[PDB]
Length: 301
Ligand SMILES: CO[C@H]1O[C@H](CO)[C@@H](S[C@@H]2O[C@H](CO)[C@@H](S[C@@H]3O[C@H](CO)[C@@H](S[C@@H]4O[C@H](CO)[C@@H](S[C@@H]5O[C@H](CO)[C@@H](O)[C@H](O)[C@H]5O)[C@H](O)[C@H]4O)[C@H](O)[C@H]3O)[C@H](O)[C@H]2O)[C@H](O)[C@H]1O
Ligand SMILES: [Ca+2]
Ligand SMILES: [Ca+2]
Ligand SMILES: [Ca+2]
Ligand SMILES: [Ca+2]
Ligand SMILES: [Ca+2]
Ligand SMILES: [Ca+2]
Ligand SMILES: [Ca+2]
Ligand SMILES: [Ca+2]
Ligand SMILES: [Ca+2]
Ligand SMILES: [Ca+2]
Ligand code: NA
Ligand code: NA
Image (cartoon, rainbow, N blue to C red; front, side, top):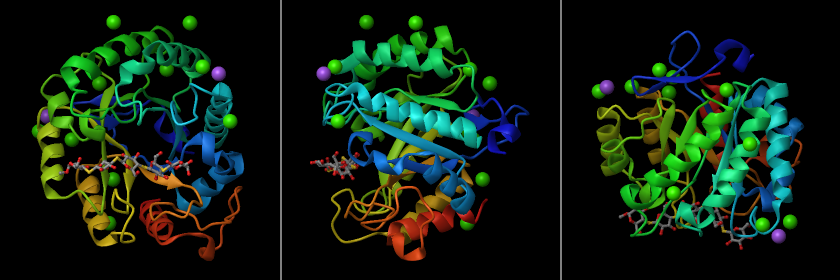
């Protein structure tokens, strides 16, 4: 039903629209790292998220480093599993080249180009797919002009050779916070969005204002990862401020994916330790974060 309704997504004047030029707002879940918590990423869990939560997008977080694709590329099969499930379930899917410790996207540029060539050849004809080419550039000397924009200008043509139209999400500096710098020096490709990531327990009004500056320059923004906890993971969840961010995103119709669908014992995790990997969760199997996020997606489903 989701993709049947919306079809091919595109960017129109800085925001995400469907095949009729209607606003569309994607809300869903990110996996945790696929090399760690892949058991939660399967057709049955994603069908449960679609049917019980109301998700219309699922994000497959394929770490590069940290034991991910660079060391054990078999994890790409878990990405394929997620994409094929999303196609079968008629929802959107984000293929995320999940850089983090490898903080400069140029570390694994050759590998990223090969990976995105393969993924876009396989899936580029499906409107379901969204590419996220570098999760979180970070560090004081990884900047838009020197490192990130040129990386994107090399990877995007690789995708476009196979998939001229699907959305590409491009990370920004300072853990995908520096959307203002990207907005002042935008990519030419018309169907790109810039990532903005936050933690409710850490980030506040000054970053909302930074996002608004970017939006004011005509840049499209996808909140492709956010957490209900603090970035430190201390002090529980911060749902008061999370609701402030939910409202902010709704008022700007910003799409989002929440971090993350795992049973790890950390406050951002959506599930309690032991939760069934194939879905069908009881209310006792959702964490406080998961309970809140589920309600946020349900109430617009
Ligand atoms: C003034 O404010 C501004 O400057 C501030 C100072 O620099 C920063 S604070 C800064 O914020 C950033 C952005 O939020 C974060 S990075 C952030 O951290 C998250 C929490 O760690 C992670 S998700 C997290 O990823 C972990 C690493 O992979 C894993 S632990 C990992 O788990 C596996 C599996 O179990 C295990 O095998 C491994 O052994 C473990 O290492 C964890 O489970 C995940 O939840 C997110 O990806 C990242 O964005 C900085 O930490 C923080 O200091 C302000 O942000 C800025 O505005
Ligand atoms: Ca357009
Ligand atoms: Ca807008
Ligand atoms: Ca390798
Ligand atoms: Ca492995
Ligand atoms: Ca090729
Ligand atoms: Ca396409
Ligand atoms: Ca080059
Ligand atoms: Ca404007
Ligand atoms: Ca509301
Ligand atoms: Ca909306
Ligand atoms: Na290897
Ligand atoms: Na505008």
